[PDB]
Length: 240
Length: 11
Ligand SMILES: C[C@H](CCC(=O)O)[C@H]1CC[C@H]2[C@@H]3CC[C@@H]4CC(=O)CC[C@]4(C)[C@H]3CC[C@]12C
Image (cartoon, rainbow over all chains, first blue to last red):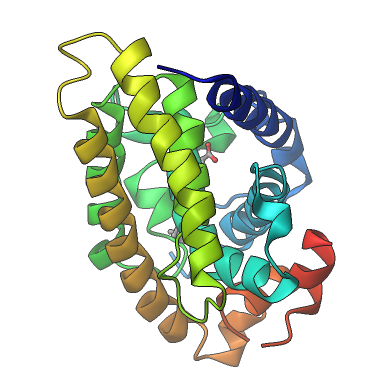
C-alpha cells in the first residue's frame, strides 16, 4: 500500500507542479506576439513560450524528492535531455481533443497544427506530437499520475552524459515504485488496466519525439538568421 | 558542457 513516504512524494510533486504550471497562462502576454498569416511567423512567439517553459520545468525538477542529492553536472545533464520531453508532457493539460489544439486560455494563445507548424519544424515532428497528445489524453491520468510521470521522465538514468547513474536510478525507482503503487490503490479499474505499462510506453514515445526534435533543431538552427529568433536559454539547452 | 544559464537556474 501507499506508505507515508510515497504519499509525501505525491504531495510534493503536486505542489511543485502547481507552482510551475499556471493554468491561467497570464505570463504568455510577455512573449513576443504570435503571428498567424508563413516565413516562421510563429517562431518568435513559440520560441519565447518554449524558453519560458524550460525555466518552469527546471523549477519543477528542483522540487523532485531526491533530485537535490545529485551533482550539478548530473542535474544539468538530466534537464538538458528531458526538457523538451517534459514540456511536451506538461502541455497535455492545455491540449483539447475537441479541435486538436493547445488551448492556453484565449484565442491568441490557442495553438493548432498550423500555428505549431509555423515555427521551423515539419510534420515529421508535429504529426507524431499530436498523436502523442491524443493518446496521453486518452489515458485520463489522475493529476497525481501526471506529475509522477514528469518526475520519472526527468530522472532517467540512461540520458546522455549521466554520471552517477546508479543514484539517478535509485531516485527514479522510488518515484516509479510510488507510481505503480498509486495506480494499484488509487486508480480503480478498468482505467487502471495496464496503466503503468501504458505510461512507460509514453516515455519511449517521448524519447522518439525528443530524437526527432533534435534533428529539426539542428536544421532550424543551421541558419544563423533563424538562431537569432530564439532565446539564449533555448540556444544553450537545445544547441548553440 | 558549460551551461551557465541552466547551471544558474538549477543552483
Ligand atoms: C503550446 C504547447 C504547450 C502548452 C502548455 O504548456 O500547456 C507547446 C508544448 C510542445 C511545444 C512544441 C515542441 C517542439 C518545437 C519547439 C520550438 O522551438 C517551437 C516549435 C515546437 C513545434 C513547439 C510549439 C509549442 C508547443 C506545442
